[PDB]
Figure (cartoon, rainbow over the protein chains, first blue to last red):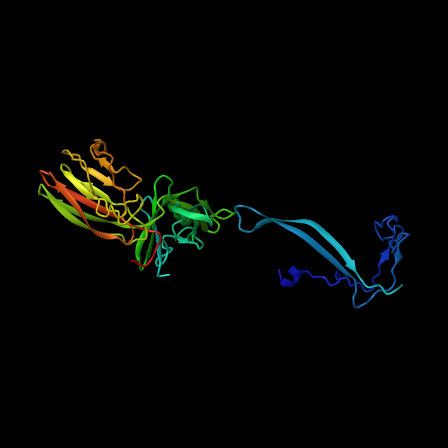
Length: 99
Length: 290
């Protein structure tokens, strides 16, 4: 098998978030299970979610994933036999313009 | 370094060079930070006095040497062989020799395992095949020794007398040992060398003690060492019983020495006297002092 066939890379699977928006809702609002409209598969935002408007372009939106890990090493092994991801913290930050 | 060479002779006769030229040839090297190795531990006594406390004498303590070694090889099987051999070189009941050789000669210390060794790292030692062993050895006799000096005087005359040259080049007093053949009446020196430990330092400058008359076959070992009984008959006779509250009391003080006189009388077949003088030092190496 040739290298290109082994790679089987698709450019269409690369998705560029050309226009991004952030919507916030009070904790009493029913959470959004999905954003796909059941009737026609369009973009359906549940009621109670309100956009934060424009935000900075150069800053963008940064999604941060932080892993807390623990190394399990055995008495009869030099390297750690296993690693445990105790927790995974998710954060996101951005710079809103509107008041 | 080539100025200092540390070796161990195990209880089984194995020879290890832990430091100096040839170190690690047997697979075991010596780690730094070894304690109570150089100076003999001595504690001083103090009694209350007008200006605080007054000096009351000193007592020497047994050595507690805590050191560490590396047992190393490229393959785990041979490392295991070396580690087993190192463990075999030690015991609690019987002692192994630890020699330090420098420009001041070779001096040895007899040491035994004070407690069980602490080997290996936190993981299994076959991974690294290069592991430390923590040794807590003890020296019951805390003084570094050299080979004792032995002198022989044999005679065929019934009455004879000789002068044994004796000298204490060490920094600590030593106790003399005599081996006297039988029969015959022996007179042995017990010179104080100025020692006032019995308030007779100069009264006993030329003190001689006459051992009891020995019957045939009653060869005696006369050791002034406080550890052992002074008179020991080889045949089990109570020779000390016929000795009337007399004893060898004085060691050979440091820096002192002379031609001590040994006299033999009433010996039909002559007699032989052997003098053993130990060479005890408080340090593995030290320049001669006088």
